[PDB]
Image 1 (tube, rainbow over the protein chains, first blue to last red):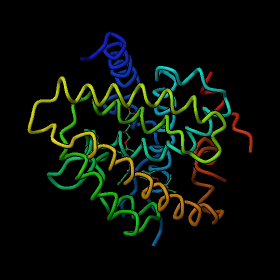
Image 2: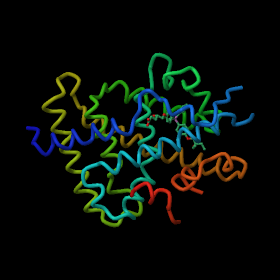
Image 3: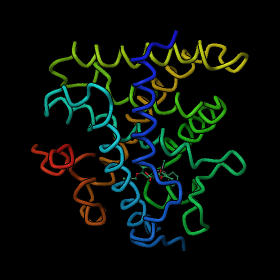
Length: 240
Length: 11
Ligand SMILES: CCC(O)(CC)COc1ccc([Si@](C)(c2ccccc2)c2ccc(OC[C@@H](O)CCC(=O)O)c(C)c2)cc1C
């Protein structure tokens, strides 16, 4: 039942991800270096990592079918509200349940709960973040489902400040129906059992994670010495 | 409340 339009969408999104996610992690050497041993010693490195990721998320979003039919203002509202969530989603590709860490090809660039703690965050965020990463990894998503879920996340019509919420909803529905039909036609049981509902629950989980990250980010970035270590793009997108 | 960097990355 996967229409030709739906096959087209999946192909575009797969290509978009391949063009915006580099699983060699070669660019990490351009970031300010990790420091692991009170001070927020990992804030410079993780700010650069996050800023880099935001650029990749914007590059992916621009390729979503229909996204560029939105106004510039609506494109900005969707990216500002979703970037944090898509970073959590896309980072699941490097996350491993072996030791609950994000392994980006190198001991320098393998991160655990202690690293994000050394950027100022607390267990109020980290504990649900890890639960989310585990629950998402356990879904064993096809790459097709992974890229559809990122795109559905970005094109959400209930983000605050959306103007043309009905066009946003129209675009998201085309993606949602593509995903629902993909699961039925290409994801064998038992892996497909309740799969779409479980993926939509992950989008709900991300809203709560967004809220707690935003709360902690506001507290951290209110201190000028912390803001000094951020990047201009992080300040624009996450807030100043 | 302007987003020149985001706006620039959106082409
Ligand atoms: C004020 C501090 C702050 O709020 C803002 C600056 C801090 O914000 C943070 C800090 C950390 C994280 Si993390 C879930 C994490 C969790 C636990 C430990 C370390 C990091 C993460 C992000 C990207 C990433 O990887 C990018 C690769 O996915 C890019 C691949 C590509 O696109 O080519 C990996 C692997 C992990 C997210 C955010 C928003």
